[PDB]
Length: 170
Ligand SMILES: *[C@@H](O)[C@H](C[C@@H]1CCNC1=O)NC(=O)[C@H](CC1CCCCC1)NC(=O)OCC(C)(C)c1cccc(Cl)c1
Image (cartoon, rainbow, N blue to C red):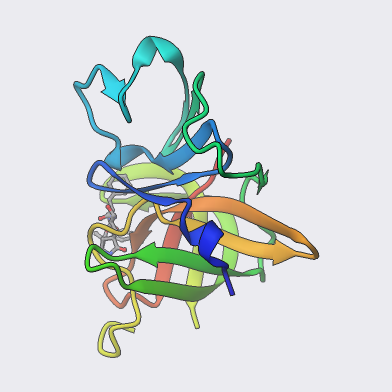
């Protein structure tokens, strides 16, 4: 059960979403990142460290962008069998936390590209329980004791919607 403040980290970005890991660290899916710009959130690129690894993009800002937030655990995927929550925001404002049992980390063929990431099985289309275009960047999270953990960003899903894929950091 993700609390309000954790959902407040999910942020509209480009053609999808991203997620504030900390006041200065923002993660998203590479294919939703806007191209051609000279700023993100009003900050000049000169003021932003960009780390990209495949479909996982991480920004570190020099300015505290979300000073209301604490840091949190960011991990490179999760162990097979982990049930994560995908914190899907829709543009209507509706929240759709999607439970997903994560499979193996691998390099997957997706729309003709090789992508490092992690598949998962929803716990779909006909029951409108799945992901849809515009959801990319939404965080995959789980709680470990008193620690919230983010471990991927939404990147793709099957025709059925019963299988999703997150990008994971290198
Ligand atoms: C977010 O942009 C979107 C979310 C998807 C769309 C449909 N349902 C979702 O959850 N992601 C994509 O559309 C994704 C974009 C690629 C672009 C290049 C790099 C990797 C991501 N494509 C996608 O999900 O493909 C859908 C299929 C059916 C064509 C597909 C093919 C192969 C494997 C999979 Cl899992 C899906």
